Image (cartoon, rainbow, N blue to C red; front, side, top):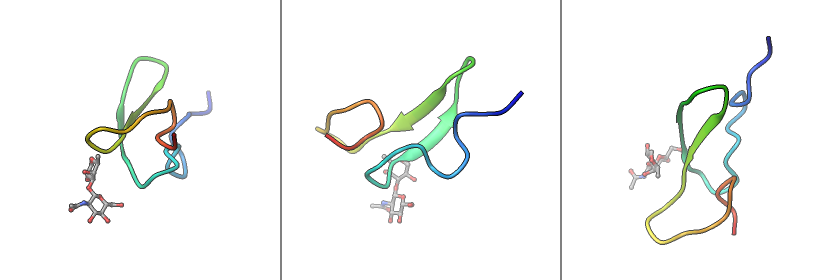
Length: 38
Ligand SMILES: *[C@@H]1O[C@@H](C)[C@@H](O)[C@@H](O[C@@H]2O[C@H](CO)[C@@H](O)[C@H](O)[C@H]2NC(C)=O)[C@@H]1O
């Protein structure tokens, strides 16, 4: 139950996709971080 990608998990205006029991935060080209922020 419950998901991970509800209100855009990313923190840099990244694209969210589908994954296996996880979230898919697609950061920009040449970025860093897990939730697209660093
Ligand atoms: C999904 O992948 C991301 C890495 C981005 O390239 C996304 O594109 C951007 O999506 C936002 C939506 O919040 C939009 O506002 C931007 O204009 C768009 N970027 C460009 C250059 O179109 C992509 O969908």
